[PDB]
Amino acid sequence: ECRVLSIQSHVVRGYVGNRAATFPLQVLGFEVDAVNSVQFSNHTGYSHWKGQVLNSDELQELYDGLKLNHVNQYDYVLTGYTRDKSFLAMVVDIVQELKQQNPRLVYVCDPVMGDQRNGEGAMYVPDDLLPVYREKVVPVADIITPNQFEAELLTGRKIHSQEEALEVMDMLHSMGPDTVVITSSNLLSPRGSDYLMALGSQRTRAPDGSVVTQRIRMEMHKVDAVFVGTGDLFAAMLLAWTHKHPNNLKVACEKTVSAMHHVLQRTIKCAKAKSGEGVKPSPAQLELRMVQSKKDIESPEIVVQATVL
Amino acid sequence: ECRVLSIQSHVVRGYVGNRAATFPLQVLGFEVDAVNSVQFSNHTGYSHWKGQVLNSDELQELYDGLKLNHVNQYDYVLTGYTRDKSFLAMVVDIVQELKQQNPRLVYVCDPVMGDQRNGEGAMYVPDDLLPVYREKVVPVADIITPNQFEAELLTGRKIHSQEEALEVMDMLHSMGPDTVVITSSNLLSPRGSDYLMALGSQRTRAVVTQRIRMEMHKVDAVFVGTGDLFAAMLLAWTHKHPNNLKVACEKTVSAMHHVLQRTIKCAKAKSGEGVKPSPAQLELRMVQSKKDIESPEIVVQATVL
Ligand SMILES: Nc1ncnc2c1ncn2[C@@H]1O[C@H](COP(=O)(O)OP(=O)(O)OP(=O)(O)O)[C@@H](O)[C@H]1O
Ligand SMILES: Nc1ncnc2c1ncn2[C@@H]1O[C@H](COP(=O)(O)OP(=O)(O)OP(=O)(O)O)[C@@H](O)[C@H]1O
Ligand SMILES: [K+]
Ligand SMILES: [K+]
Ligand SMILES: [Zn+2]
Ligand SMILES: [Zn+2]
């Protein structure tokens, strides 16, 4: 019996935030309680979008309702994109209260702030969120899934190589989370320029005070398209697989990355078919084919091997 | 590839409204766009509840977003509990607009009315909603899932026997919906007093008519969201068996039985011995009934009337 409290955005159509995360965890057997931080018609990749947002006060209201009914017991808390600092600070109060009641609670956090869109690096959020992520969110997180840019920002250090990447991940471990996964980087991969390189690290303190650190590298073949909600889907499946393989980051990452590959291959195939030959698929046509990937999400065939570093 | 627009309530914890309908439809292979009419912490069966309600203007603002992006093309529309007549009217406008764009669109409606436990923080459904359902909603609905009390209100008639029911169901057809299903009645099953009787009727312009009856053994507990789970699965099964309401209902009702059995068993297991299960312990074991929803073992035989 595992219950997850997921606080993320919601869209009527498409897959992003809680939409990208709920279905996967449900088919994997987790009980998901979903707080929708906002409700829009579709993601911001489209030309238009309309919806409402929740302020930190409304969030607190929803939590008080769970608390008043004595059902505020969770095994996992999962958060992603957040645009306002009050909301984020409010989330930390919540995570801390819950951890006070369940020391075994695991907080999976995807510190969303930006990327380097093919050599294009800029922020998605107000510069005032970074201090909150740095000083208040990271310290209580158990698993974080930043991309290169977010790892550089959290540590204030820049990554130019695989070696510096590992140092940055160590600095992150020192900030709190025992598990760190850099989901994507600008790093050149040894298998080819067309491969995306991911890196993972899981720290473990031994009884005698010694520290064991499992580090792994992953190389996935790039799909020529820009997807949305990919980081959310990743964080959600990583939570499920790390649960099953608690002390094996290797297998957890392999199962997670394999599933991504299957979902995306099914998505790019359907998008090109729906947009005609020659024509480039539109954001509407590139929405993740979540529902049709059920079997692949439940039991993915492994198609990527993690290299132990 | 089918796409469903479901406009219902959302609750952080538990299953009612959209929470009871989405997972089921998704595992059955349907693309579900969900508009959450409200967002509460839990349903009204609990001692407390907090949340916010979405007004009709906000509902229009969302649908507009879908329109501007030319992605407002659906195959089904699914609605349930509403306590705002203003919101309900906006839903009818949205449906007629969608039906003009796709005449083949199917509107599945569960006209909720009464002192029902729900996910919109309400203690009752305003009496002033009845005339809205009667005149604006039902004429546009293709499949309706009223319970006996609701059917009686929509027709002004009162059901005292099995013949009386078929009589009301026919009236409902004439009002618009080609498929009607009275989900539960006070009617005494010949099978015993511990069985709940459900009646179903379906018209096909060959105009033909198929009527059915089902006995379901009562479960000694009070559940919330069952009406929502029913409508959602009926939607899926009617799609797979378009002209066979017998088979469609048999699978829907079977799935239901499996979910409730798994729910009552776990609830008693989690509560102390001789301790009555609390609403929180009675929340539907949805995620764990995945295989039973995808492929339910038939445990009921619908008799053709
Ligand atoms: N084009 C792609 N080809 C292959 N895998 C991809 C692609 N885009 C995303 N992914 C996969 O999705 C997961 C998350 O990707 P990435 O690290 O780019 O996300 P992100 O920058 O956090 O996402 P977002 O910007 O949408 O929040 C990774 O496991 C990655 O392999
Ligand atoms: N105690 C029970 N035992 C067996 N089946 C039940 C029970 N309660 C509900 N159901 C099943 O749930 C479905 C809907 O039942 P019911 O007539 O109570 O719904 P409703 O009035 O639409 O629901 P709601 O409580 O959401 O208003 C039917 O298929 C019915 O058999
Ligand atoms: K990420
Ligand atoms: K009903
Ligand atoms: Zn991201
Ligand atoms: Zn009902």
Image: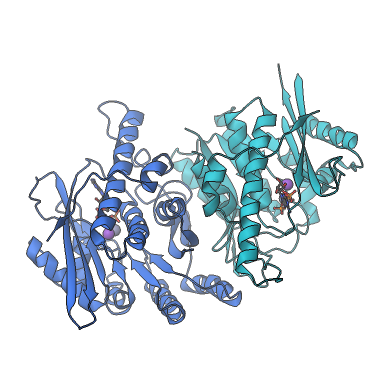
Chain colours: A blue, B cyan
Q: Is residue B126 left or right of residue B234?
A: right
The residue at the far top in this view is B206
Q: Quadrant of the C terminus of chain A?
A: bottom left
| Viewer-proximal residue among B261 and A254 | B261
| Viewer-proximal residue among A182 and A215 | A215
Residue A149 percent location from the top left of the image: 19, 62
In the image, residue A99 sits, relative to residue B5, either above or below, namely below
Residue B53 percent location from the top left of the image: 60, 61
The residue at the far front in this view is B273
Would you say residue A158 is visible in this rendering? no
In the image, residue A224 sits, relative to residue B289, either above or below, namely above
Q: Residue at x 43, y 50 (%)?
A: A49
Would you say residue B121 is visible in this rendering? yes
Q: Residue at x 84, y 46 (%)?
A: B153
Residue B18 percent location from the top left of the image: 57, 52
In the image, residue A7 sits, relative to residue B85, either above or below, namely below
Task: Report the number of numbered marks.
Answer: 0
Q: Residue at x 54, y 70 (%)?
A: A62
Residue B242 lies in what quarter of the image? top right
Residue B249 percent location from the top left of the image: 68, 36
Q: Is residue A307 left or right of residue A100?
A: left
